[PDB]
Image (cartoon, rainbow over all chains, first blue to last red; front, top):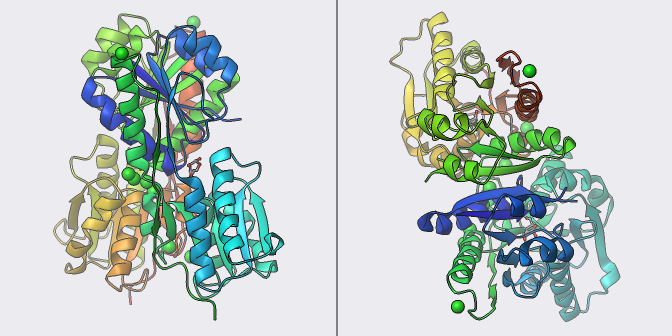
Length: 268
Length: 267
Ligand SMILES: OC[C@H]1O[C@H](O)[C@H](O)[C@@H]1O
Ligand SMILES: OC[C@H]1O[C@H](O)[C@H](O)[C@@H]1O
Ligand SMILES: [Cl-]
Ligand SMILES: [Cl-]
Ligand SMILES: [Cl-]
Ligand SMILES: [Cl-]
Ligand SMILES: [Cl-]
Ligand SMILES: [Cl-]
Ligand SMILES: [Cl-]
Ligand SMILES: [Cl-]
């Protein structure tokens, strides 16, 4: 009666809210939900030995080999999502990353920003990469040369956003796409400390719509993933797989949406 | 080789940072750390799964469940935070009474005499100790226990947000929020009501989670040594596993005042 959830980063509200959505569904079927913070030790092997019944895997740190050796051999069904690539004989839930990046780009470009900084994790996971590709598709619509993107790779965290502020200030960028909300919060701090204002000096759009977006000032404009629902959907898929081992293999895709708040403005 | 960490609220950065401190130590001894959000039979199920030891930060795990599952099956455990002490366990605590006292003394030194307490309804004992410490400070300044504006709410950003209207028509000029998440709720509520911090309200929070340094003004707060708390809890458990008959310990770690920019002298 135990389901294991493997995430890249439990300190990110995205993954704790994901967990809450999972728990919301599993609790009703008397499953215990446990969470592992697995980034880049044999998590799967140990948890499989402990008799964990099924897994929900959101991290790329869990390899195909580890899944084959432990989950498949021992008949433990699993769901993949988020940073984890698809696997044979698993169900998946994904959100529309390409679309979300496209929406972010189109918003900044509609406001007249033409020199734009991209704040993103060095060596991004594939879902994050797809956001960047969608953003570049928006640049193509506006015929912005891809080398007018100011690339600001950093650590995927508030601290990482904070640390690239000096580079942002030394660039000609007027708008910023932060590849998650945590990165954006880092930028807020850096810009505040440098005596700058949002949106007067910089338009910023983030990604996820974690709750904190509504508690900072100005409130952060962002691409909303349906985070809680993503967790619920992953849990429902797993319960259905446990109840119906031979049901159709599914790769569900949930939409994102633009959440317009007060961290962007037309370029003057 | 698996250790179970039971927390009351994984969405609170306090508990995810706690977890990171625990992992930091356990990882080095090749232990797998798993986390449960517990506020059904967690212990019974995880004990059956062969979880080797537990770190229990939630009061939602009962003495009976511990006896029936952990003690019977020889699984050592550590208690902390919201969880009360248990026989034949080690504990690590932070100085809650002191922290509340520091918060009260700070607001009172600034001239605030009508103060609001924003706290969780049905507070756990550690949070109650903070409130008692705060009241001790009010005693030093001979503030009746009356003026104190009592604003119980849900233990969350949303809870802090939702008691803002109650705060606004009180005579309070200073606020002690019983954690940083509650304080963030107040920021949002006060901003939307067109108020300023600290010009209209002095606010002091509790925990010193990372976000305190990313909001504006930066939040004045009582720091718990969160990461170190997790590390200490993990070290105690490993020592108990290596030395089952070592001294039973109740470690207590200090708190400290983090003065930032969300308070100011009353004008
Ligand atoms: O915010 C954390 C990011 O990493 C994950 O991949 C999530 O999709 C989220 O956007
Ligand atoms: O911030 C969460 C609070 O609940 C817990 O009891 C912690 O000590 C912390 O202050
Ligand atoms: Cl969230
Ligand atoms: Cl949040
Ligand atoms: Cl803010
Ligand atoms: Cl949702
Ligand atoms: Cl959500
Ligand atoms: Cl079937
Ligand atoms: Cl400040
Ligand atoms: Cl011993």
